[PDB]
Amino acid sequence: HHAPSYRVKRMDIAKNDEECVVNAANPRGLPGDGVCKAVYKKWPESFKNSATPVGTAKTVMCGTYPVIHAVGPNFSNYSESEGDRELAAAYREVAKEVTRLGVNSVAIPLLSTGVYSGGKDRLTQSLNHLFTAMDSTDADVVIYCRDKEWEKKISEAIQMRT
């Protein structure tokens, strides 16, 4: 049968072609910044009762279209140690949700790499926690970013594995 893949697109995640989206949410279900705010402009109804704790994910149905609210840690608040564990946990919940939904594909941004980055480049950290959780799912995963340099590195990381 199908053959689950990983791909990267460098474009706006709100314009994704996949069966469901993962929002880089804040714990309080707020419009927020960057990806989360792009998610809010496109799918504001998905923010109804979407607030959920750090390290978890909460799905809100927007019609038949699932929005997976995943709360990665803000490294300005979490130590590297605790944060690492929360970023892992957040991704783990994405995998369980994508599984529970029976979805064939999902679009995902790199959690905790922007406003939550604490000033640090976290491409490899976040990507790696993404693989570790998603590698056991069979959904087609499409990773979104905007930076040209970031796309290339994520592309290299995908191709190097297969």
Image (cartoon, rainbow, N blue to C red):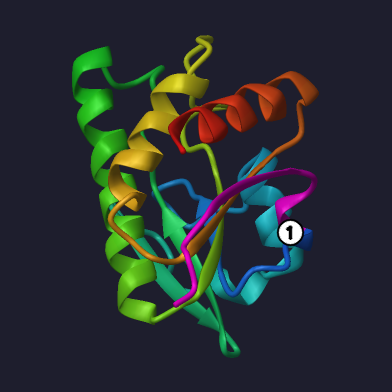
- On whether residue 2 falls in the magenta region, the answer is yes
Quarter of the image with the N terminus in it: bottom left
Q: Which residues are magenta?
A: 1-14
Depth check: 148 or 27 in front? 148
Q: Is residue 97 left or right of residue 122?
A: left
Q: Residue at x 26, y 50 (%)?
A: 92
Depth check: 65 or 39 in front? 65
Q: Residue at x 39, y 68 (%)?
A: 98
Which residue is labeled 1 in the image?
A: 14
Tell me if I can see residue 115 in this picture.
yes
Q: Residue at x 29, y 21 (%)?
A: 78
Indicate the secondary structure of the residue bearing disc 1. helix
Task: Examine the image and state in which quarter residue 145 appears.
Answer: top right
Q: Is residue 40 left or right of residue 159?
A: right
Q: Position of residue 42 (x, y in %)?
A: 75, 66
Residue type (three-letter) at the residue carrying disc 1: Ala
Q: Is residue 118 left or right of residue 72?
A: right
How many C-alpha atoms fall within 10 Å of the one at disc 1: few (<14), some, or many (≥20)? Answer: some
Tell me if I can see residue 74 in this picture.
no
Q: Position of residue 110 (x, y in %)?
A: 52, 37
Q: Position of residue 156 (x, y in %)?
A: 60, 25
- On whether residue 160 falls in the magenta region, the answer is no
Q: Position of residue 124 (x, y in %)?
A: 46, 21
Depth check: 20 or 51 in front? 20
Quick check: 144 above or below 103?
above
Task: Examine the image and state in which quarter residue 49 appears.
Answer: bottom left
